[PDB]
Each structure stands twice: as structure tokens, then as C-alpha cells.
Image (cartoon, rainbow, N blue to C red; front, side, top):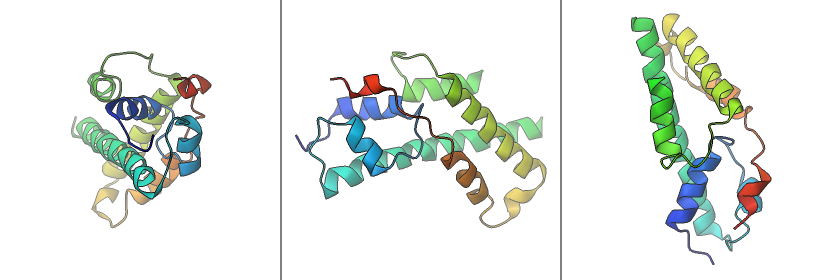
Length: 139
């Protein structure tokens, strides 16, 4: 079918633990049950953009906290793994800590008052995607 469902949305969120910047090609490989077209492809792609938005908002918030001075993972896990179906992968943790460090350095260094200060961070994180587990391909 060409219609995205709540199940696809739930699956997409779990996949975020491996891929923050999946290409259309990646998405097609892992969603073999969908007949991709311009509309649903963009719709699926938009979801990961939403996922990243929430992710970075949380990353910056926590980093500012640290500077101004467990819950973070609870927040991330509730959002992307509500029913706690999967174990948070170690590589996601490394990406989270790496992201926090990028924001922490920037904020602590007062670089957050510069234009495009978050771009250098996105670049770094976009290179840290992990291959999506093959089991995600199973119905």
C-alpha cells in the first residue's frame, strides 16, 4: 500500500535509535511493505525531521542545564520507545553523549550567540548514523 499508518510511525520512531538522517534509499529498504511515491516518501522523510527537531531541542536544553549548574534518557526513551519494546542501543548513547558535548562546548564557549552555531554540530551528528537492524525489515 501507499498509505502510511500508525504502525509505520511507531516503527520509524524506533529506527531513530539507529538513524537520525536516513536517506530515501534507506527508508525504502526498511519499509519494503510500502509503495513509495513523492507524497509518502516526503511524509516519511518529514517524520525524521520532526524526530531530529525534538532530539536537538532536548540536547540543547540539557547542555544549557549542565552549564548553568538519567532524566534525559527517560525523556528520549518515552518519546521514541514508549512501550519499551527495544533496549536503547549503545551506539545511540554514544551519539547522545557526543551531541551533548558539542552543545556544551558551544554554550560554555558562548558560541551559541553566533549565527549557524548549530550547523557544525548537525554536520558531525549526521555522520554518526548506524545501520538499521535487519529485523526491522520483517513484518
